[PDB]
Amino acid sequence: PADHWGIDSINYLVEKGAVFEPGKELTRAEAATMMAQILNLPIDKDAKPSFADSQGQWYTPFIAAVEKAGVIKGTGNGFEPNGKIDRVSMASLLVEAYKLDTKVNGTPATKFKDLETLNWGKEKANILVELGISVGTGDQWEPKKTVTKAEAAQFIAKTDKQFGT
Ligand SMILES: CC(=O)N[C@@H]1[C@H](O[C@H]2[C@H](O)[C@@H](NC(C)=O)[C@H](O)O[C@@H]2CO)O[C@@H]2CO[C@](C)(C(=O)O)O[C@H]2[C@@H]1O
């Protein structure tokens, strides 16, 4: 929709063939697929990723591509392609895909109460904040909240337009 948020982002992604169901929650496999396409990675049809849990499905060669490019690791217990992706995992995808750690000077400050107490991925969220890719709300960044398709489009369109090649 025209005056609706996300439209310039989604058009950018459509223009680059990387993506309406904007409020739909995104799975980790769908996020990885958007990455594989925006990065223009080579997609070998029968290439398989390492992960036992990511075989035999439409997303499988896309996951293999972003694993080969170093963009995804597992969770440690596989890739969990059909689990919903949360914001801190999204951050991890973008930081790895675009080497965003080389785009900031030193270590970004922590600007949110709920990034301070985080088990993993604090640094990656802070980098997104530092780069203004995540605007962030008030005093909560909500690292474990799931990402919608339109929110993913914004993160990716914004990041790629700035740092893509
Ligand atoms: C192996 C590793 O450290 N992975 C990180 C992360 O790994 C977490 C566990 O989630 C996490 N497991 C749980 C159940 O929370 C574990 O406790 O700590 C690991 C880090 O020490 O998992 C992310 C999953 O999503 C992506 C995009 C991904 O690449 O799939 O990014 C991963 C991070 O790189």
Image (tube, rainbow, N blue to C red):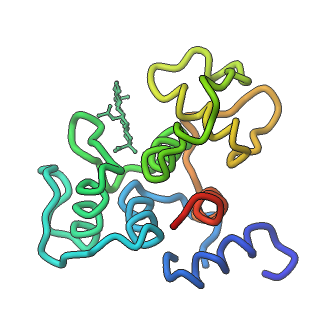
Residue occupying image coordinates x 67% and y 80%: 11
Measured as percent of width and height from the top left, residue 102 is found at 53, 39
Q: Left or right: where does residue 49 sit relative to residue 87?
A: left
Residue 117 versus residue 33 in the image, above or below: above
Residue occupying image coordinates x 30% and y 49%: 70
Residue occupying image coordinates x 26% and y 64%: 65
Measured as percent of width and height from the top left, residue 22 is found at 64, 69
**Number of disc labels:** 0
Residue occupying image coordinates x 75% and y 39%: 136
Depth check, front residue: 147 or 116? 116
Q: Left or right: where does residue 55 sit relative to residue 26?
A: left
Depth check, front residue: 58 or 154? 154
Q: Left or right: where does residue 41 sit relative to residue 116?
A: left
Residue 40 versus residue 116 in the image, above or below: below
Query: Which quarter of the rendered picture does the N terminus lie within?
Result: bottom right
Q: Left or right: where does residue 129 sit relative to residue 85?
A: right
Instruction: Name the residue furthest right.
Output: 3
Measured as percent of width and height from the top left, residue 7 is found at 74, 75
Measured as percent of width and height from the top left, residue 23 is found at 64, 64
Residue 159 versus residue 107 in the image, above or below: below
- Which quarter of the picture shows residue 6? bottom right
- Which quarter of the picture shows residue 123? top right
Depth check, front residue: 58 or 162? 162
Depth check, front residue: 52 or 110? 110
User: Ligand 1 shows up in which quadrant of the image?
Assistant: top left
